[PDB]
Length: 222
RNA sequence: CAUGGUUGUCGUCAGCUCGUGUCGUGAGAUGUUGGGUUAAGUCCCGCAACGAGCGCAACCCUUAUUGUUAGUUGCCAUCAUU
Ligand SMILES: [K+]
Ligand SMILES: [K+]
Ligand SMILES: [Mg+2]
Ligand SMILES: [Mg+2]
Ligand SMILES: [Mg+2]
Ligand SMILES: [Mg+2]
Image (cartoon, rainbow, N blue to C red; front, side, top):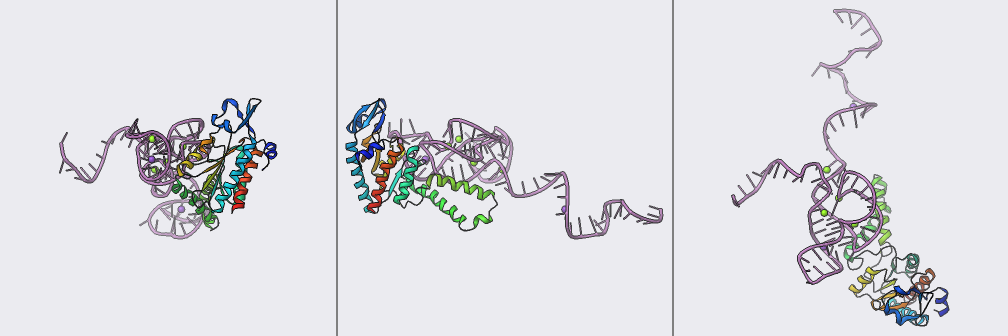
């Protein structure tokens, strides 16, 4: 990935100065118009390191979980994870998604069961009220667990856009010792992320560019 | 004031909890709170929770309309009679 490609996508824009994390100075180039400008020279080095790291993860056949619920990130991380063949969370992270995995599976299992009825003919002999109700129930589960519905186990790596926003996802990863690859903004804490990518979290073309490379890495490694 | 069973009572009020997860040194907390809504912990949305059980509701009885089957010991519209 090119330094101009990052610049065109606006990967350099940080947050307002007063809202920074002091630990991010290591990745900041300068400040402009009241905002911190990320150092793209290190961004290229770090995104390449993440690219190889994600690849080496896929080579093992391990699972990757793309987490991002930001408005800017929600559409991309869905597309790329499906594109890469991996699993994603893009609407809302459920507390216990991974730490409470056993209980969560009973809900993913429910989704499979209700999908079966539709492809089994039970909905044809249902008294309207049930089928309408179970359709709503299926819709909610797909709303939440659809992106991970087919995840075979707890992921070997988690990719997070705006880890500051995705606070619970970072906590569930630390608990389970799942390394995190994240786009880290000027306001985010880098010490919680094993593979840092200093990047803007608030520009769609910025999230699309970085997410695509990480998704491609999993395509290439597998 | 040793008990089983049975009963009143708050009160047909809406609640009472559990499993797993998470927070807390700990007792505990979370869920069950919040924004709406409902007769209702009723439902929806939001949420470090995700689900489940006992309750709520429904399934039961009666009452209000009606088709059909039945027509005596019930009934008398169309008939003659008392
Ligand atoms: K508990
Ligand atoms: K009848
Ligand atoms: Mg209560
Ligand atoms: Mg209830
Ligand atoms: Mg709630
Ligand atoms: Mg009842």
